[PDB]
Image 1 (spheres, protein in one colour):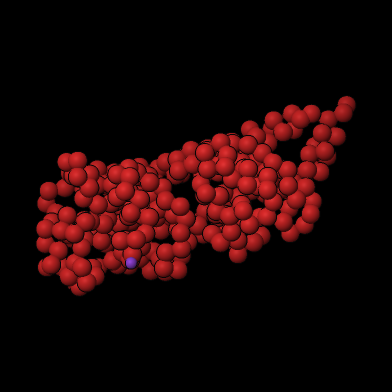
Image 2 (tube, helix red, strand yellow):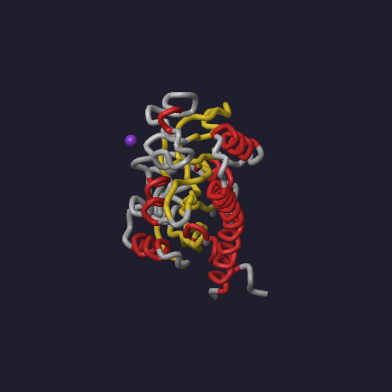
Length: 271
Ligand SMILES: [K+]
């Protein structure tokens, strides 16, 4: 027993759930930014900006806040704002308020005609917690929510988090003697890691090499929690991965437990 397994699951789950609180709340902020923009008649760009700016300022964990509208969708005055502060050649209302370099500036969004953070919500007309991407230097993840104006898609409202935040938080976690933990996106990209920050956002469970690892990639794409045995990459010692879904977005929290250390666990139960 084997109630060893039972107990790692239970913890894996606990964590996954703590990180759900965090991610549920972020999305709530986006859903609220957008339900609001749906209800916004005035359509004063500065007032918007204020809202954005102030939600960033008041939510320190947030990489940035933003709104982005379809051509003229915001206030019909797109050709007016062309090239003014916080816009681009288009004059579309696409203001991104962000801490991207300690400094809390605002700037226009980039590639909103091609990036998930916009296109997925436009295609699905539903909320999204995007896969991690490398946007203009930083690896972040966006919680975006479509602004539906009377059954018609007017654009998005969102907020960002950096992986660098995530990893800071996750690599804290320890278990047993050598055991740790990492998050992973819904397609199994690596979101955090205690000793190889070079993997973050660059490798997904398919690169970790093995074929059982491809199995668990499917469980996590479906938000199913399970476990495997596998050799650590940097050393051949068998470890057990316990992944458990993070409900919003269906990411996965993976707990790494050294196969040994569990035999050591069970031993310490003989008297
Ligand atoms: K582009």
